[PDB]
Image (cartoon, coloured by chain):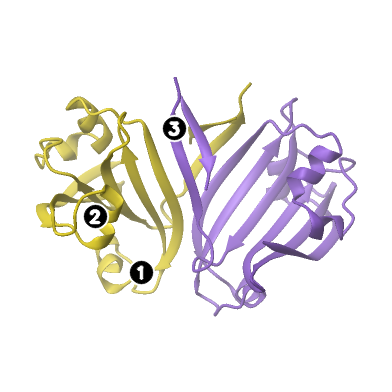
Chain colours: A yellow, B purple
Amino acid sequence: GLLVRRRPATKVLVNTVVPATAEIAAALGVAEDSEVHRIERLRLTHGEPMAYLCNYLPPGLVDLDTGQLEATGLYRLMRAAGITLHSARQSIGARAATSGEAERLGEDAGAPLLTMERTTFDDTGRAVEFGTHTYRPSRYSFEFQLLVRP
Amino acid sequence: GLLVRRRPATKVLVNTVVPATAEIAAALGVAEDSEVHRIERLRLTHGEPMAYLCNYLPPGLVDLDTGQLEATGLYRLMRAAGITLHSARQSIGARAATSGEAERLGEDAGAPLLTMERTTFDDTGRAVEFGTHTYRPSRYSFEFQLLVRP
């Protein structure tokens, strides 16, 4: 079996409620146009922008107060509200940035970005969080160790 | 603790012996300019190029016959020669492709590529393999599941 070990400042840009598109509904297992929470954060290191984090949560899970979010990570907050985080599904990829995300991060439109999409589930196998993220490749990379564990 | 589960055709382009640069020596724990094996593979899916794989092995580990390499994966071959693979260190990133890798893969110079670097160690904690890879982001992504395991 394969065990894993993974090898900044946060500013909230969006804290809203929104109807689920098909992609979001699919990820979270809710109905299209049902309401979900949309959060957007910029993460900076040494005052420079590192990553752009968009997250979607299903209704009635957590109190999403902007501010709490600038203090601690989203997972810590969720556990704090007594959500159990049991697994996550992840895909890591790369894209040319469109004008929007290129601006938010301080980069030219078309410049390569590191992307990742994640869905997080609880004890009962329900999606609890869906994230769609971009990272400045000159500023960030996914670092981990894989271990064969008896 | 965090367990992990991961969610083509191969053509050998280079099978050679080469002096270690500082980067390669560092990864593998050998001396600069000491000799290492350099392998290069193109992986294709449906006859289209998916990834460009450069690997370096320290001397006297495996018989690296081109051909065997078009049949099976590099890890299987190494285990086959009785190497124990115990862990690996990985970093995943993104780059604009330079003319070289852009050509090899069928892409314009500057087009975003998915990159990954990996070092693999055996039972005794020695590097056994160092890989430096590129992936066409429209053709590939890193897919996995993370599990909290009692």
Pointer 1: what residue? Answer: A97
- Judging from the image, what secondary structure is the residue with disc 1 in? loop
Residue A50 visible, this orientation: no
**Which residue sits at x=45%, y=62%?**
A94
Q: Residue furthest front?
A: A31
Name the side, left or right, on which B47 lies relative to A130: right
**Of marks 1 and 2, the one in the foreground:** 2
Label 2: element kind: helix
Of residues B114 and B142, which is closer to you in this image?
B142
Tag 3: residue type?
A: Leu
Tell me whether marks 1 and 2 sit on the same chain: yes
Callouts 3 and 2 in the same chain? no
> Relative to B91, does residue A134 appear above or below in the rendering?
below
Are the residues flagged by discs 3 and 1 from a single subunit? no
Left or right, A140 with respect to B78, comes to left
Residue labelled with disc 3: B147
**In the image, which is nearer the foreground, mark 3 or mark 1?**
3
As measured in the structure, the alpha-carbon distance from the residue carrying label 3 to the one carrying label 1 is: 31 Å
Chain of the residue under the numbered disc 3 shown in the image: B
Residue A10 picture location, percent across and down: 23, 44
The one nearer the camera, A4 or B57, is A4
Residue underneath mark 2: A25
